Amino acid sequence: QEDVLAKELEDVNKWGLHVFRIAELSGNRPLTVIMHTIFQERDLLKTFKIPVDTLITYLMTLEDHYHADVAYHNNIHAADVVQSTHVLLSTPALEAVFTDLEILAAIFASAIHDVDHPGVSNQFLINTNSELALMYNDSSVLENHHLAVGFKLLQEENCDIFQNLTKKQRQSLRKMVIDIVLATDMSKHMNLLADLKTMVETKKVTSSGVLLLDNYSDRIQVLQNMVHCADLSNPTKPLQLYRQWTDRIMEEFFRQGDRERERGMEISPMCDKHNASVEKSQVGFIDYIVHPLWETWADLVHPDAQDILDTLEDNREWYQSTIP
Ligand SMILES: CC(C)=C[C@@H]1C[C@](C)(CCO)Oc2c1c(=O)n(C)c1ncccc21
Ligand SMILES: [Mg+2]
Ligand SMILES: [Zn+2]
Image 1 (tube, rainbow, N blue to C red):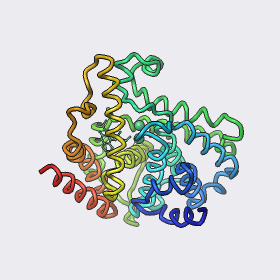
Image 2: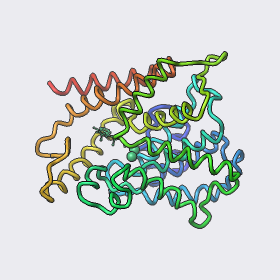
Image 3: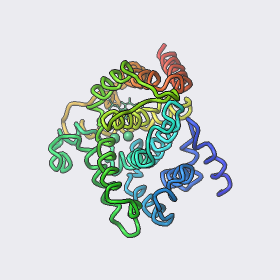
Image 4: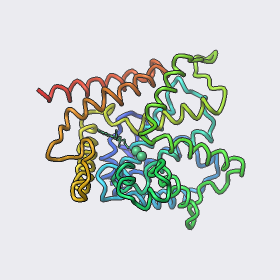
């Protein structure tokens, strides 16, 4: 089985890697083997003196703290966002733009960006007076928790994969990781897209035809939208993968609606299993959220993302076709 897994891992540089098949072949360790594969591909172990046994130990511990009984926000989703971010980092319009520390931060942020997700939304945790909403004062409750867990696990035995970074380097990475994961809060999507459009309008390139980023504000803004695009990348994948992600998020939404109904609360959108329209929700999800975001990203890295945008529009056309 080790040979079959190594064959599938050869697609790690490709959009639409079959991450579910990799989860099978790796014994439900997609996050660990995909992160390890990416770290070798980018030669991140030698650059930052990361001991290989420290890396595997942390990745296994981080993967354990993703809930296996949550349908969508599990370790497969984490591995999917890591691998999608890895491909977006390699796009020609961004060649040699980001340093090795920014690359490490963006990939590490993707790996921890949903750790210990309980399968319910921020608003549910706020409305139900949960301990998490109490700890974090109703502000980016899940995203603050993911960061806290992801950093604390570095202190477990033989788990500090940043042990050989300089104190300056650790200081810069920690701030960049926090800025990125906090930007995955869906309540910040509109402001994140609005700033991304302003950058597309005022786009500037270098003499090598490569995106020019002068300052931390523009650089972290591109990294924020990149991980945000990978988080919202399910409808841009081949349909057989997209549909599996749709089935998983609808199961998670339906389970929250059952808890909302059992508590006497008003059911959140798309969460009532007795009056849900999966196809129309997917169409509205693409039209109002996913396509505006990816169309803007495609303008930023034009024409590198045209095939991804083509697949998204074909999938939107298909989900529409099932309605009549
Ligand atoms: C809460 C809102 C507004 C969006 C969420 C964002 C989320 C959780 C991002 C991944 O962490 O994924 C999807 C969402 C959603 O509403 N739908 C319909 C989806 N359909 C198919 C696949 C993923 C999603
Ligand atoms: Mg999240
Ligand atoms: Zn996510």
